[PDB]
Every structure is written in structure tokens, then in C-alpha cells.
Amino acid sequence: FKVGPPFELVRDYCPVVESHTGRTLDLRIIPRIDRGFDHIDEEWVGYKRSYFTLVSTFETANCDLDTFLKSSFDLLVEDSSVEGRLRVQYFAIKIKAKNDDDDTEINLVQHTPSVCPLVPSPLPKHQIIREASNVRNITKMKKYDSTFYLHRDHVNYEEYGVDSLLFSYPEDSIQKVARYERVQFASSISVKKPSQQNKHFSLHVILGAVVDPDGIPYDELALKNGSKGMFVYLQEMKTPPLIIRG
Image (cartoon, rainbow, N blue to C red; front, side, top):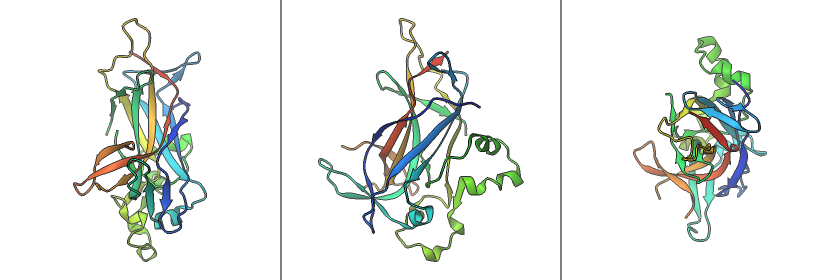
């Protein structure tokens, strides 16, 4: 494990507002790469046969988790789409790899990326990510449970309303930290141009809202009840240019 390529803001997309208070939700993705890249003379270098670890959470400025989970949020589209407000079923994160030059998407292979549902939370320290990674100790894993998950089936249900965000999440076990362990680039990718000069890649992290089937950037998504949902972009961050040794 080691300090990896830093993340920078790429863009903020659709604004999110609470349906009851009209309060705008201020969001901030907090991603970090914990291994897989070396910093050689002002350049980040990765390797084909190697793999990398990327973790991420997101935060909501001045909004405590309890209130957040009890709230209802609407996405605000505008102009062309101008639909108005789309109800958020839940928030999730996804990562992608791109050709930092022509912005072409590079496929990633993970060891089990995917759309990870997530609730606001600070990003755990580097060492904790380790002690929680591949260390399946029953007692130990229970010391990190409150750090990595929110078990909806344990909250006081009488405190939440029918439209509460908590109850629109797909599963009872909800992650607090999106952990992408053992990720590699597809072995089919070309890491050099015909001239033999290195190609440049970039890792992206996108925070988004999953909304019901019914011009804005989003990905089509296979929901939980067989329905076709939409993963609408809220915020995106990326690493600086990366090079991949073959």
C-alpha cells in the first residue's frame, strides 16, 4: 500500500434538493487510491499485471446522517430536459478508466466495477482500510462493522416516513465506504501509441443519484426489481494523467 494519484474536481452536474425544506444538498466525493501506482519523476505509473485499490465515500456539508436518511431528495434538471424534479431513490458511486487524451473509455476488470449504493460518511484512514481488507477475523470484522456499514433493519422504523431515503435504498445492508479492491485494466488495452510514446489514462470517480425509469449525463442501470433505472451524474473527480507499463 502507498499514497497514490490525487483526485481533482472535474465537474458538478445536477443540483439535489430536499423535498420538505427545499434545502440544497452540498456534496463532496472523497476518493483515494491506496495502492498500485508509483510516482516516478513527475509521472504516475501503473502496471498491466498489477492491480490497484481505490476507496471512496462522499459527504454532505452540515447535514448529519440521521436527518439525511430521514429526508427525501429531488434532482433538478433544466432547460432542454426541463422535466423539473426527479425523485432520488438513493445515491451510489462508480469508477471508470479513460484515455486521458481522446477521452475514450478503457475497460476495468475487478476481482469479486459496479454501481455501489452509499450513505454519507468520512473516509477511514489508510491503515484501517488494510486491517479491514482481507482480514476475515470474526471479532475484528465486528470492530469495523459500524465503520463500513449501515444496517437498515436495525434502525427504529417508527422514526422514518414512507418516502424516507433510507427506505428507497435497494438492500438493508448499506455501505458507508465504496471499496474497490483488486482492480486491473483490461489486458487487451494498448498502453503505447504506434510511435512508441506512452498513452495517457485517467481514473474517474462519479457520485450519482439512481432514479426511476420515468440531454443530461447518466448511465442506464439494471435496478433491483428488474426495472430499468437511471444513474444520473451529480459529481465527478479524476486523477491526473497516468501511464501504464506493459
